[PDB]
Image (cartoon, rainbow over all chains, first blue to last red; front, side):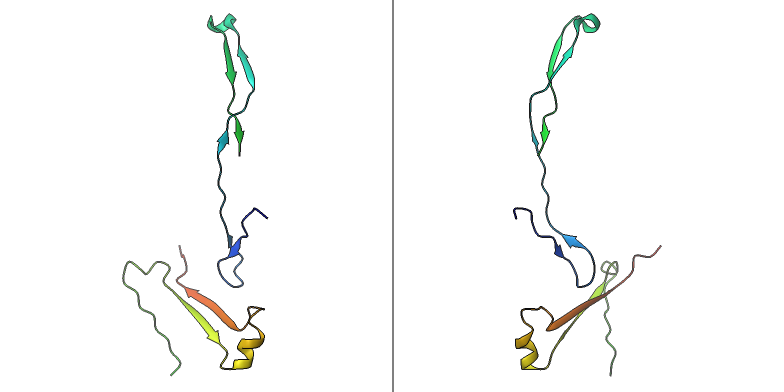
Length: 51
Length: 51
């Protein structure tokens, strides 16, 4: 269990607290913007991946 | 004889609270329920977040 164990804050309360971190790891996804509307093409690698 | 009084300054009024921890006055009760976590009992009384 790499997930942290949510520890209750009080006896018979119902609130459990832990920790959750997030980051962005870039990935590859080609998006083509034609030159018919911008006079210059754009090959865009998108956001990435949420981790 | 049975009254407890908690007084807090102006800045500590929001969420001022008392936690009561009752422990057995018995050696056997401490020894036999250390693993179960039910040899001391704790509860809390706090100033409610009121509208």
